[PDB]
Length: 288
Ligand SMILES: CC(C)(C)c1ccc(C(=O)Nc2cc(-c3ccccc3)nn2-c2ccccc2)cc1
Image (cartoon, rainbow, N blue to C red; front, side, top):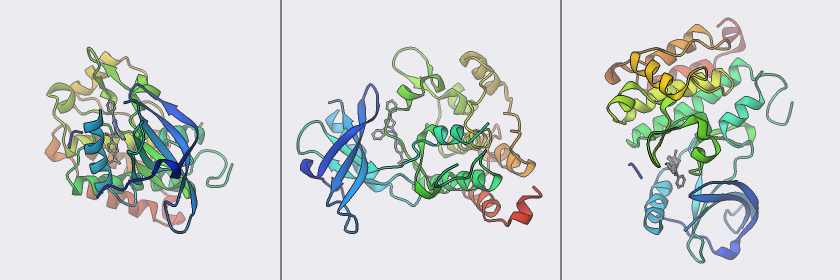
């Protein structure tokens, strides 16, 4: 809400079970029939609105607008019978924070043990690609963090969420008075102090996403309370270099974390550097 529509017949959606819950809705896994030509049956994630209606139409418009190779695919809505539904792509590894933790200190998509440096960089690059697209359309996320990315088959990583991160990951937010919940640990000085949010508050957040990736999904400033974390951020402390993170990747983080918004590197450059590294041969990466 800070920044055409496909429609799906209720009968074509068959709910299977709940994936998660919140204050403003529930998410289910469902079979969707006649959605794509190739697949006559297919799995999808369905967001059910608690039941509001105006916001829904507006959000649905924007979600349909924002479609990219690294943005969670939105198929359309179901406005036939209440409750209103939003239909998204099903991403089988769930959110990126959960995926990182479950492969940190085997299977179909990933090797045993912690994810190697090349895997971590591929993840980083895809999220960066996603924010390039968003910056290019001049969309400000406001809550970029690994919990708001999803991991699919073949370790495809895409930006997107179902609006329940405040409920599932409540410790990642600071309740400031009543009903406002801020992802302070992911926010730069200008958002905490002045309450400004821009493309460059998002680069900062990406920098913190990069730290999350390289710490296997650990919470930023985990050693601190919320007030202590606000103190450190506003006073200008930068997160330390993760053990798994080599100097050159850490240098990418710091460019995201320049205190002054204009001195931060553009997302396009962050991506270009991370892609290169992700697409670099084992001989070059083994030496990083
Ligand atoms: C990356 C894309 C463009 C796909 C994107 C960007 C932003 C959001 C988003 O803004 N999500 C989001 C936050 C809350 C939210 C709820 C309560 C309090 C504070 C924030 N709801 N939603 C939500 C609502 C309807 C559908 C899906 C997500 C999603 C995707």
